[PDB]
Length: 51
Length: 50
Length: 50
Image 1 (cartoon, rainbow over the protein chains, first blue to last red):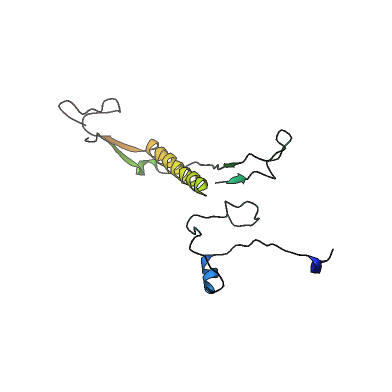
Image 2 (spheres, rainbow over the protein chains, first blue to last red):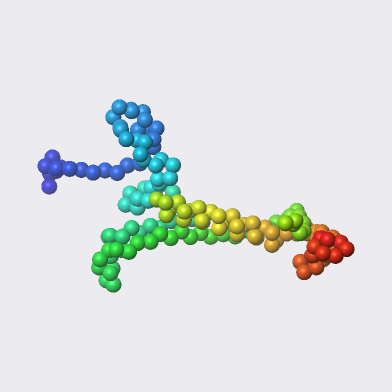
């Protein structure tokens, strides 16, 4: 019953490659991910208003 | 279109299948056209060389 | 990911094919090459190939 006692919290959000590339040092291993065909249609748990 | 993906594991559970194993993905749509000026469509029928 | 991509590509192709078939069916002005008057009369052999 206390958020301070919680061990972990997980959040899913939508982001684009430009947002990650704003700060290149923090993010690594961007080359492996298939940006050209990976879509949020593949992930149904995320609830959003995007078509 | 209307894409619907029910990945197996929590939504595919059922009385006939308590064990979520099955999934699917369906895409459906409506379609129809209305022709206003038929005389403006022009067609030529011909044979094509091999 | 690959399965979803191929599904979507098939859907788009089907929509385009149906639209093209409808447009060809609803043509207003038609010509037949040569002396032919319908689909049956169109021929390659003869004095006047279509």
